[PDB]
Length: 341
Ligand code: NI
Image 1: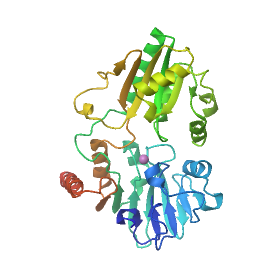
Image 2: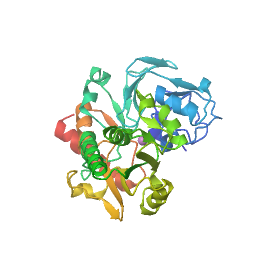
Image 3: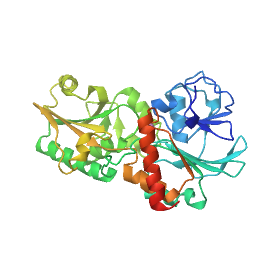
Image 4: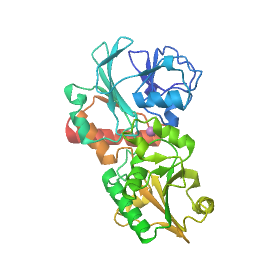
């Protein structure tokens, strides 16, 4: 059944709850972002109102084929009324079109649901500064102090410098970037930009990117692989066999591959700096795992919550085991005692 952490009390609303059939009592289904665990269950046969950002609405229409009449896009940073309840959508700093949702309940309670987010100090000057939030439905993906990672800026700097040096030493080296969802487009765009190339990709991935309202996108991507020296591939193909394979396909236009795998966290975060990363190498193929995260570090999350001072926290991630639940509740109490709310 639909878990309690997907239901908004005192409304008929649910968040990211599309794979339970009809939820008894649900009058409006909100969708925070277009990632498959969140949208799972949506299709052309859905006949209930879906509320989401413009970008998530373009993807529901074009990639899932949900019918236009059931898609209700809302602008960001704007007080809107949905079935008689005031709501605001805020940028989540996750993937394109990802939002947080503020619900103002008729009883006076204010609820923030973060969806998936990477907390940032800039959020402390959004419409959240304006009033008190009583309950927080929190993205707890990396709620443990071992999870450190560098800034997005630091990681992109590294990738840019690595690629530019490699291709300048060898003009017949190909750059390959893995992907399996929207998100992390800065990685392959920033590399393409320093190399004076457009990024080349499959027809399905191009279609996906043309939904995202990226400015000048037509100048930055292409379906013609041959003209491009930054290729996107399915993340599954980012390994030596898949890359050798792909290398044959280019018809001797390249003799070397430099590949990036943008991971979340991986245990080498606990021992190694971004300046000191090294790749896995087999012949003329090298693979860098780079820790580009679109989720809050432990410290970023802690700062956000200690700023917001919620009365109650409901985790939405890692909720499946008693041990995870208990560990999370311990950190929340530490935070509250240190900060005095
Ligand atoms: Ni996500």
